[PDB]
Amino acid sequence: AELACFCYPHLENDSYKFIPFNNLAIKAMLTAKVDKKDMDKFYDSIIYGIAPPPQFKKRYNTNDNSRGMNFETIMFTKVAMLICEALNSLKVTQANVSNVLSRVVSIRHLENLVIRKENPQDILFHSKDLLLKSTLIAIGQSKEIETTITAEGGEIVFQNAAFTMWKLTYLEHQLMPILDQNFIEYKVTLNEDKPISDVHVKELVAELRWQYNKFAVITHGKGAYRIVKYSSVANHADRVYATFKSNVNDFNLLDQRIIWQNWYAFTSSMKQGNTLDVCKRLLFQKMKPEKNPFKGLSTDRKMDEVS
Amino acid sequence: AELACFCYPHLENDSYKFIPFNNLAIKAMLTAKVDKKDMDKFYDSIIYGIAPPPQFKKRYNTNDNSRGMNFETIMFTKVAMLICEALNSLKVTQANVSNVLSRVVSIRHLENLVIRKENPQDILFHSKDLLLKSTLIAIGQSKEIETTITAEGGEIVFQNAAFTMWKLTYLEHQLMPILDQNFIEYKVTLNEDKPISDVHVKELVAELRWQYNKFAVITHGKGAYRIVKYSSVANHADRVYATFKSNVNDFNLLDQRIIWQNWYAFTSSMKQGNTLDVCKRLLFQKMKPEKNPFKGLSTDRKMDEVS
Amino acid sequence: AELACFCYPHLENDSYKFIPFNNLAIKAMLTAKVDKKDMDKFYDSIIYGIAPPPQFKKRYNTNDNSRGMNFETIMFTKVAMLICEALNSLKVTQANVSNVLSRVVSIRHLENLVIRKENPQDILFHSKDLLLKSTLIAIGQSKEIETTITAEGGEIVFQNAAFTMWKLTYLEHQLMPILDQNFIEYKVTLNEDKPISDVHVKELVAELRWQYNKFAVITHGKGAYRIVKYSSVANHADRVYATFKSNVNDFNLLDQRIIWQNWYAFTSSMKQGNTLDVCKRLLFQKMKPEKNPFKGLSTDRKMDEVS
Amino acid sequence: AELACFCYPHLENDSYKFIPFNNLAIKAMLTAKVDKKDMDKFYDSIIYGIAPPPQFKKRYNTNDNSRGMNFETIMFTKVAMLICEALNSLKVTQANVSNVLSRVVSIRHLENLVIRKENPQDILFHSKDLLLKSTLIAIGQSKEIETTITAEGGEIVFQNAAFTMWKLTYLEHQLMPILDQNFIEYKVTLNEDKPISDVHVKELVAELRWQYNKFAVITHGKGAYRIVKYSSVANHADRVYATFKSNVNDFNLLDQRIIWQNWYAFTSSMKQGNTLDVCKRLLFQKMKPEKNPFKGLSTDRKMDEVS
Amino acid sequence: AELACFCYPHLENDSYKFIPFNNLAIKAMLTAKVDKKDMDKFYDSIIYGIAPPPQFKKRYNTNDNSRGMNFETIMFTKVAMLICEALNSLKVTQANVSNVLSRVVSIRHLENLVIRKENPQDILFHSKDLLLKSTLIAIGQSKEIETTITAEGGEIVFQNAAFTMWKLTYLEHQLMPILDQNFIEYKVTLNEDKPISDVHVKELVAELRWQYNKFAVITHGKGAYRIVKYSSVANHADRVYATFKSNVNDFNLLDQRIIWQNWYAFTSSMKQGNTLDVCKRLLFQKMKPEKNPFKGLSTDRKMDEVS
Amino acid sequence: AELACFCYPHLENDSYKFIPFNNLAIKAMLTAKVDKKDMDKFYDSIIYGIAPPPQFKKRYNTNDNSRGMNFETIMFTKVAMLICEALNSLKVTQANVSNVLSRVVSIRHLENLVIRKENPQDILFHSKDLLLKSTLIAIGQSKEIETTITAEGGEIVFQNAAFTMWKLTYLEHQLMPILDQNFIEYKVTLNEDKPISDVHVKELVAELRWQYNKFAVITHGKGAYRIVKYSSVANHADRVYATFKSNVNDFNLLDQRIIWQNWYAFTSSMKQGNTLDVCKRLLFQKMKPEKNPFKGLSTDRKMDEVS
Ligand SMILES: Nc1ncnc2c1ncn2[C@@H]1O[C@@H](COP(=O)(O)OP(=O)(O)OP(O)(O)=S)[C@H](O)[C@H]1O
Ligand SMILES: Nc1ncnc2c1ncn2[C@@H]1O[C@@H](COP(=O)(O)OP(=O)(O)OP(O)(O)=S)[C@H](O)[C@H]1O
Ligand SMILES: Nc1ncnc2c1ncn2[C@@H]1O[C@@H](COP(=O)(O)OP(=O)(O)OP(O)(O)=S)[C@H](O)[C@H]1O
Ligand SMILES: Nc1ncnc2c1ncn2[C@@H]1O[C@@H](COP(=O)(O)OP(=O)(O)OP(O)(O)=S)[C@H](O)[C@H]1O
Ligand SMILES: Nc1ncnc2c1ncn2[C@@H]1O[C@@H](COP(=O)(O)OP(=O)(O)OP(O)(O)=S)[C@H](O)[C@H]1O
Ligand SMILES: Nc1ncnc2c1ncn2[C@@H]1O[C@@H](COP(=O)(O)OP(=O)(O)OP(O)(O)=S)[C@H](O)[C@H]1O
């Protein structure tokens, strides 16, 4: 959803400070009869403050919408406040307020940051600087690449001198969980954005083949690996393409010894400018088996097990 | 009930400050043997403070009274305090204390104000001035007309540039709910007491015919519409008449394009001084169908639905 | 689903007797690796009997399918037995077994018949002849028209000398309920398929305008009225058209004073052979208001209420 | 309610056999649109059998009626069957069917008989003859006087060689309990309708003064004492009068040493033909204290206690 | 129990300050092997502080004692603190510490004072002076007479210009409730220890005969009436005698028009110095009925009821 | 455990009929003081019948034994009866009774047969002949090889024209479940003990690599595959060896293209007569990768997924 679904602008000494919406003001808005000429204008509930532009009605779950977010939960407020604390430290101007708020961000990524922020064991609970950087990345107001320190978090299922593998807890989310109960997905972040040895790539690749053999190692190109069911690569190919198509934009293919062969092809075809069908095609054909970089990984792990 | 059911007067530097009753002192009073010459005098429980005049015994629910209020709930205290905070800001004199306290007010209206007052999302939670004005109106110590800002509240089911429609939550009240579980009623307040366009009246009327076709649009004449079941107009006619009969008094017929035809007649007959039977009669006859002000409203909404 | 999802054929003295599937045999089948040349052949579980042809896998809900039926419930068995008791009384031949079983029937309609069949207050609980006729109609092996006696049932919300209005209890179904919790739909059956007076049509039409004003009176053309939300007429138009398109077929427009104006147009355009767009178009335009057959109905009911 | 609220007549070999109503047929009826010329005619639900004449709608509790009976409980069926088993043994004729069914009987009295009938410890559970006589008395098709054997039952709180005192369990009834939770009432039946000694009257009177001092000993004149709160004598006086007024009739004043002084006066004034006001008046005046028949009773019981 | 069951002495600047026992130190003590020469000496648990003299083992409930108190409840601590706050304000000396602590007090009376003390509606919650006086009376370190203000409290069932009647809530006590579930007892305190009119005595006596006819009005002679079951007067006679026998002492017969005839006799015989048998005898004989002071009380109340 | 833990012999007309033990007789036995010369003799409880020889005390779980069985569950009885129904159909003689009962059988295998036997969907519920054969195999009184029809059962996770793969439900067993909650194990039975094509072996092998990559395909040599965690092969190697060592014996290596390479080696070394260390050694070394029989299986399944 747009950042304009969580807060509204407010002039306060030349600078713009962002304020969170009360869920009841949103509720009033969803029952309000607005003019087509005001759908893009914030709404005054009179009783519970300002509400989002009524043109975003589809972002909030109601009795006939389960495709939006659960704005009546406390997580909506926590997430809104997180976005506000971030935007407030930018001192946006009377000309970006619009561009900034119309930005679409990942809700699951923000709620995941709230979970990190509130855990006193998480480093984010203690560093407003790290928390800030983590959030700016998520709301698209940063140039940095998400790494382990600034990751959205989740449950750690594998740690290496080079990477940290997380199990995404979207099914358990309060704000906008995933409805498909068969959902399983993992994210691998780079601990440090520096040179990674072969022994550390081999340690990870081995873990991925043995522990997650039914998963395809892909990437959305922003610096982290995404471990998803093969029966889901298609949908990912579509979303990443649609995104690339938005030229109006950098992509990181990541380590080719880790990314699934077909995904690397599909993505390189895309980075070369090709069409969708041309790309998608590559993703389906049983390409020529590349020279396995780390052979034996499977057998070794298997033998260790046997002891 | 009388305001004297929630508090008692107390001289404190020439001015009169009102104090709330402890529920246990009320309980003692209900078991007390008082003299007919003291029924109008406050009662001393000796143990829990001062209690209301024993002549009001019928206002409190007991084992043989369900026609009163649940004074042992916390809502009784919250409501009492609300009344006290209001009266204390008037600095009543040694001659009105009686007149003021003998005033009958709507308990459901006060408990509704407590619910608004305690919600941090409601503007009343932040404006003691607005809260004050809202309460003074309710306890009859104000000249202002209840509008959206100062309304008793409830659940907002429709908002317009001109009105706000609330669903009265009386069934859920702790202090003195409605016992009839088949009860449904809505209130429409004017957002601003100023000139209202036709397009905004049409937006409301359309909503009332489509969404509440089994409801009659009436008014008790204090500036707001009351949406009630047709099978309840009779009782309303009686209560509003009885009230008018109390000449010892202004009435607002409100917009004639909104108020149910028969109700407007019944009320105008009343504002002209007529009798009850003369009025009630008008309310039952299938009067001549007036020239529909906004024709087509029904069909339009219906067609929108179909898309 | 196809009737072949509930039972399988079995030669037994020249005649074909149908046997119900065990849910565990279906489960085995859903885990079975079948050859593309056997997808249309019944499956042997070896342990729990015969299962349906694996080409119907999509009819049964699993961890990745919620678009099918809950075959593990007792209702699956009850429904299967109902279908079997019906087919067994036909003595199908070695040439129809296929045609008969490949017939698609409404599961909600069958489960509704089980609910009637098991209630000792329902006449079906006592007439295997009426139960039979009711089921044959539902499984498409009958020429008769569903009337009140043979209806699928539900909760009776209005009864007339001529019609009976039922509230469809699909949300509560065990076998294949409706997932959309905002679903509300009613069915009106003719008590007797004979001449219906005007006073009895007027009694019904009045009830439909007052009690169900937000509902469009339509029909799927098999002899009964379907009362659905206007925001659902579109989907109905599609399903009825798709069905009509299946020329490889009779349609009953029903009483034109009852069916919604636009639906009658949409359907007559269809009975004339027209295209989809040509028809659908009629359904959206605010046609010229036909001469109201029973005027005043609204006001009368309203006045009765007021007493 | 009328006996016609539980069953309907049916010719079966010159005699009339009564059949119980299905609760669902009653429900259909309550939603049926009947003609004013058929309100007194049984109703055909088409689906659940015959229902009572729609003119009795007020006898059944619905969403807007709590003044009737809970016909959907099993007790409705049990009670209906009890009434049927009784009427069926009378072989009513083609001319009384109406008179018999229009008879108003006490529902609480019948449900009380069902409770006795189903307890294997109660003699009624074993004597269909005694059960029959008990029911005929209750439905007004008998000349006998209710005594201990044929009483409606309840909880036995005192037994004497001459009487049995029962605590009426109406608050616990399923079919038509009493809604006023402050209700307490007892009934005293004569074990044998023969000469009762003074020592046995004294034993009872003593128990009534010591154990039930806040209760007035009255009677509805059908042979049993009714022990009710003094704050309820008024309502009883009205109901017994209204009943007496129905000349279109015998009354038993019962033992004058037991019946409350004022009640005996009120009732004798009634048996003499007087008006209501003339009677009611007697009930309120502090009449001249009659010569206490059994003096000392109080002190004795008190002294026994002290040991 | 002795006050020495709740606290122990401690020299602190010439004065003696009392400290509460930890329940765990009591528990240790109950498992301790003490010498017969130390049974009267406080016990050191080493781990949880000082405990009471092991000679009081019988005051605490254990697995084989239900005749003591539940020292592990919070009420034990609250009660101990109440006793401490009282004794600490006396500044007892190095010669009374023993006499003071060996004093037996009523636990139910103290726990009742804790309940008053903690209720913010009770005046004791606000007056440490009144709380103090109330406690000193209870622990026998005061000359004052318990009146309504300083009563042990309970549920108020009747209030008069002169008296307040309380229902003792011993069954609900945490520290040392009454085990006999059939227990019911009331206490009547004098609001003011001054001249009481006849009309106010008559108001009370009337309430006692009508509302509590099975109760004997007695007194333990310390200024308040005790309303107990006649089947309990005997036990009371014994306890009051045993107490009187403790000459090593003033008694208040109270109003003779209120106290049960026999109790007044039994007590006057005692105040004259007589033996137990001589007294007890008076309590059983059906003495000559004294000239009823307020005749008619019964009939009046009865007549009021009837209206 | 020994079959002598479930029943005892009894001469009845030259033949020996087996009777089940009452759990209470076992309990008595576990508290009985027996002589070392009777430990092998059945025990008479006197009160609950005959119990097992006290030398088997270790087979029953008590307060200090969790290594046995839960003989107090109904499953103990059901299992005992199953064993009895089997032995009774053999008509054992006065010379085998001992040999037969001292036979150790798998309890989990028997309880699994009870679960099949009681399910009306399972073929065993209908064939006492098949049930019999299945049980005789399990208790070691049969020459037949367990196949799908006669398998111990469980949850079917894969079915082929040639095999059926079951998930062992030992964790859920009542009689003697597995305590290690991390336990997962599957069994693959041959549907028919006949020639199996390559396409059907390939279908299975593909399923085993994709769906169970962390599992080693082994066998205990009685005709079925056992799918266990690699971290469990060691324990299996020990149990199968210990068993082989019991020469006082046939082994089926099964299809070498399916059994894990190392397991085939370990087992062939055993079938050749070798020692334990010699065998175990083979199981650990990373043997030379044999020529993959069905290459590509992995990639194909993976590609199918992607569609
Ligand atoms: N309802 C939705 N649920 C999930 N994704 C959506 C939804 N709607 C749009 N998207 C897609 O979200 C993006 C892909 O999913 P995300 O996980 O949100 O991307 P991402 O968070 O940037 O990826 P990472 O974290 O860098 S590996 C595509 O740009 C969008 O097409
Ligand atoms: N127990 C009662 N319950 C509800 N109304 C009562 C009751 N007793 C008296 N009334 C009536 O209360 C008034 C009408 O109901 P209310 O809703 O309280 O009026 P109101 O609150 O002033 O109306 P609004 O808010 O201006 S539309 C009549 O003056 C009284 O007759
Ligand atoms: N999953 C589905 N749920 C509901 N309807 C479906 C579904 N799939 C197909 N249909 C449609 O079912 C038919 C319309 O719905 P139904 O209620 O089943 O028809 P119907 O039961 O014959 O109508 P009646 O009872 O005569 S008014 C259309 O022929 C189909 O397109
Ligand atoms: N809803 C009602 N509840 C109780 N009584 C009613 C009700 N409606 C009418 N009655 C009265 O019922 C009768 C008195 O109550 P009942 O207890 O039913 O009489 P009764 O059962 O004949 O008295 P007994 O058993 O001989 S002492 C009066 O004739 C009626 O006025
Ligand atoms: N376990 C016990 N339970 C109750 N009373 C006891 C117990 N043991 C001794 N007593 C008696 O307690 C006294 C009478 O009971 P209490 O109610 O405690 O007296 P009291 O509290 O002084 O009376 P009041 O309050 O002035 S009317 C007698 O002096 C004792 O015999
Ligand atoms: N407590 C125990 N739990 C499991 N197995 C045991 C236990 N005690 C002994 N065993 C072993 O049981 C055998 C192997 O386990 P099982 O599964 O019972 O064999 P099995 O049932 O014959 O194998 P299948 O069914 O033919 S593949 C070995 O012969 C024994 O060493």
Image: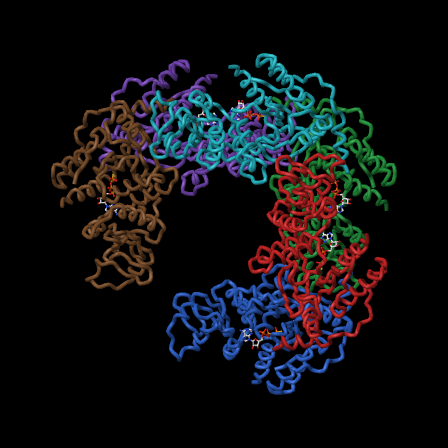
Chain colours: A purple, B green, C cyan, D red, E blue, F brown
Q: Is residue D62 visible?
A: no
Residue at position x 21%, y 58% from top? Answer: F40
Residue C113 placement, left or right of F115? right
Whether residue D284 is situated above or below residue F189 in the rendered picture: below
Q: Nearer the viewer, residue E93 or F206?
A: F206
**Quadrant of the rendered structure where residue D229 is?**
bottom right
Q: Position of residue A116 (x, y in %)?
A: 43, 38
**Residue C154 picture location, percent across and down:** 59, 34
- Quadrant for the C terminus of chain B in the image: top right
Q: In this view, does C291 lie to the left or right of D117?
A: right
Residue C120, given in percent of the width and then of the height, sits at 56, 40
Evaluate whether residue D44 shows in this view.
Answer: yes
Quadrant in which residue F258 is drawn: top left
Vertical arrangement, residue A69 with respect to residue E256, above or below = above
Residue B198's spot in the image, x, y percent?
74, 25
Q: In which quarter of the image is ligand 3?
A: top right
Q: Is residue F262 left or right of residue C78?
A: left
Q: Image check: B249 left or right of A126?
A: right
Q: How many marks?
A: 0
Taking the spot 58% from the left edge, 18% from the top edge, the residue there is C250
- The relative height of residue F92 versus residue E129 in the rendered view (above or below) is above
Occupied quadrant, residue B283 = top right
Whether E72 is drawn above or below E289: the answer is above
